[PDB]
Image 1 (spheres, rainbow over the protein chains, first blue to last red):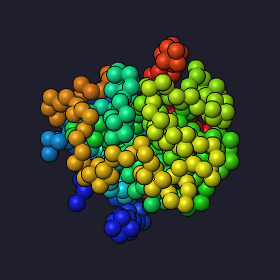
Image 2 (image 1 turned 90 degrees about the horizontal axis):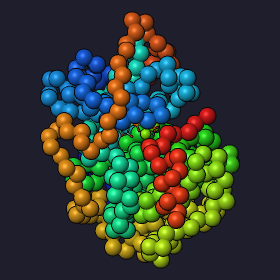
Image 3 (image 1 turned 90 degrees about the vertical axis):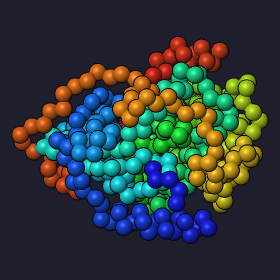
Image 4 (image 1 turned 120 degrees about the vertical axis):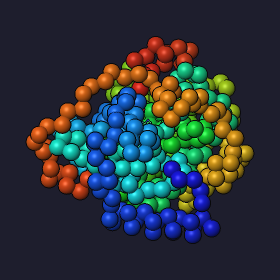
Amino acid sequence: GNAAASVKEFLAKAKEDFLKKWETPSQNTAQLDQFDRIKTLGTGSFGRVMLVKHKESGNHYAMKILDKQKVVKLKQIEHTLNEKRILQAVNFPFLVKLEFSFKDNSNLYMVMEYVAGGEMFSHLRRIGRFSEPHARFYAAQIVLTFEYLHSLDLIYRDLKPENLLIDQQGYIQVTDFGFAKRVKGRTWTLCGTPEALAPEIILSKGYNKAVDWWALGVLIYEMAAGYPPFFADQPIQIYEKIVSGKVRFPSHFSSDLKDLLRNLLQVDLTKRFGNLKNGVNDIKNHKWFATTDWIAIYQRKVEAPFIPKFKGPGDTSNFDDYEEEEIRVSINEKCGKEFTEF
Amino acid sequence: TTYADFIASGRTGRRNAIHD
Ligand SMILES: Nc1ncnc2c1ncn2[C@@H]1O[C@H](COP(=O)(O)OP(=O)(O)OP(=O)(O)O)[C@@H](O)[C@H]1O
Ligand SMILES: [Mg+2]
Ligand SMILES: [Mg+2]
């Protein structure tokens, strides 16, 4: 996301900027034959993201390809429209930039900045766990990003290391807006990733942006422990644990970290941090963040825990290898009406 | 250990979203 150029004033301008783009989204800003597709960077439950080279500029990008028929099969039409409409409208240092979008007969395409440092996930699993200062550095960026997104009436709904990328300065970029939604009241969809679901999602109650603050508790736990607070071999066993909501902490967790996590991983919405009278400030002013200079994080002035190794603009060494598949495009348009606004 | 139990589990790799 673009680098930094009162907080109430900042957020007011940010909302004006967002709403102009929300109300009149960008469409059709590239086409498939403007890019050479090189290699898959990642797949998720819905799309495939490829490293591509834009021919006329020589620039590399990360192209998310969604098969329209798969989107329909998995009941993701509205979610995918949400994803693109929101991502084209947002602007924050720790959000991946959508550079182009377009569609063809078969697929939807979201061409992002290529964030070359890899998923946080891979680094996390390899090293085992992050130190508290390292975890805190990443967590601060998510706190600020959620303050931004929630101010726009957005809920993010898929926070996990697989959807967080490390950039060339060692800062985070959030990707995968697939479950992001602009909502002023509560919402009901069962979506996310099992380990990160708040209890109120699992219990079908109706929920709001507090589920993102829960998920931040899960992320901070997982970064600092190396495993999630609620794990099992199958999702249903995870849900039981979440709803039990007893949390146990590693021996090495600081008292401050445990206290913060008890307040984020809080089943009682009247007590969950992020969800109280003082909003995000209960988190920012928590003892675990006492060392965090919030403005310096926003300005990317804090020294990063590590800068990924980068050997040229098309280097993918920080990403796992994936099986490749042909990108088919039918001579017949699929799902034209459904995706008219994309 | 909790770590050993996690590592021996089936969910140490990249996790899929759930929906529907
Ligand atoms: N801008 C990017 N630069 C580099 N790699 C990226 C970028 N965006 C996404 N990726 C990679 O592609 C993967 C899939 O992208 P994304 O998470 O958006 O797909 P998805 O199908 O919606 O995944 P999910 O199962 O979480 O819903 C990411 O986990 C990451 O490895
Ligand atoms: Mg994803
Ligand atoms: Mg997704």
